[PDB]
Image 1 (cartoon, rainbow, N blue to C red):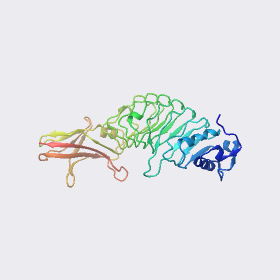
Image 2 (image 1 turned 180 degrees about the vertical axis):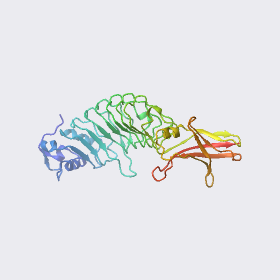
Image 3 (image 1 turned 90 degrees about the vertical axis):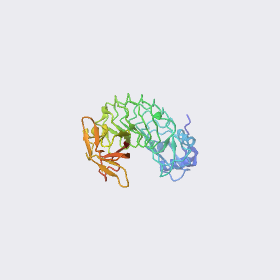
Image 4 (image 1 turned 30 degrees about the vertical axis):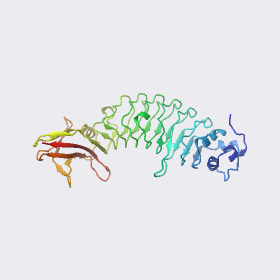
Length: 336
C-alpha cells in the first residue's frame, strides 16, 4: 500500500534530501543513513519540517511510512515550491495542521485541500501566506473546531457558507480584505470570530444564526453601523470611515448620523465618551460638538464659518497610549 518495508535507512524510506533531513531530526537520528524500524515511527507524536527544498511532490513521500500516533504537523519554514500539505492516508490520527507565518518580507502561497484522510482534525492554521483559490466548504473534517486564516489576502468570494463543520468554535479571518460576509447558517457553536483589519465598510451582515457567539472582533474596519443581533459580542477600539458629504447655508449647524458611536456607548465599549468635531487647516480647528442619543446623531456647531469647502472629521474613543487610531469619520462640508 506504498509502505516501505522496515527496517531500513531514512534516506531510502524518504528519498528526498530535504525531507529525509527533517525526518532524521523528527526521529532524533544523526544521519539520514540511520536505520529506522516501525517502533521508531510509533513513538512519534509530531512532525516538523523546515528545509525549503521540500516540494508538494517530495512531501507526498510521507505516505511511504505509517504514522500511527502523530497528532500534529508543523511546517515551520518552507520554499515557493511547497504550496500545500498533501492529503495522505498515513496520518490517521492527525488533530492539528500548522503552517508558521514566513519571515519579514517573504511571500509564500498556500492552497487548502478538502481533506478526506484527516477525519479527527481539530485545528488548522495557515495564516501569513497568500491563499491560492478559495476556502473549500469542508466535507471530511466533521470535528474541526478552530480555523486560522489571517493575513492571506482572502476576499469575500473565497469564503463559503460552511455546511459540514457544525462544531467550529473559533474562526480567524483578520488582516484580509473582506468587504462582505456570508450569513452563516450552521455555525451554531461558533464562539469567536475575528474580522479585524479588513475592509468592512458602512454596514455588514447582521448574523441571524450565531447562537453561541461571545466575541466578534471588528477592530480596524470601516463600519458606520454595527449588526444589532450580535452587539453584546462586539469589540472595537479603532475604526476609520466616512459619512456622506453635505451642503449647508452659512450660519447653520451640521448634523451627521453615526449609529456606531451610540451602539458602542450602549455596550460600554467607549473608553472615552468625548467626541471632537474639527475641520482641517495648517493646524486643525476644533468646533463645539454635542450628541443626541434618540436620533443617534452628532451635531457640530458649524454656524461661524465663512463660505467654503471644509474637510471635516469627528474623532472619538481617543485614549492615545492603548487605542492607537481611535475612531475617525471624515466628510467634505460645503458652505454657501
